Length: 79
Length: 62
Ligand SMILES: [Hg+2]
Image 1 (tube, each protein chain N blue to C red):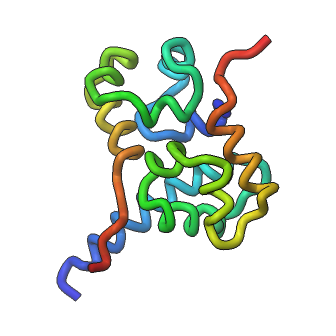
Image 2 (cartoon, rainbow over the protein chains, first blue to last red):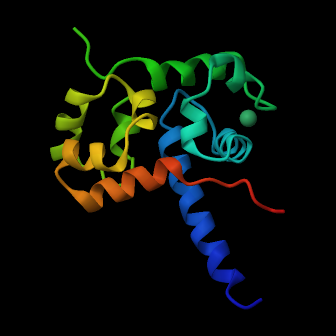
């Protein structure tokens, strides 16, 4: 197709970067992450989300839902 | 949770420090404007990259 092909490429690239972030979380998947992203639409909605909303993403523990809510909400600074 | 932060676009070893200082956690990252990110990173285009990563949405497919 014309450069729908380019839209596809830029789309995959972006998404695959989102996966680089999320798969940082304690074994939370490439799959988890693509689903996550497409359900929530943007990382902004994804982190504005409660552990409850996260668990509504079809698939995904409430286990995986906790781990991720934490990484996102736990503060950068501790000691 | 800094492992997360660093793989974020327009974030590098230098500014991971500075940014861990003015924002509580990742969640709060959602909460900032582009200008507030620029000032916190001192790089206007780094701020573009990270702000865009965060605010880009799928919600189309008509
Ligand atoms: Hg999911």
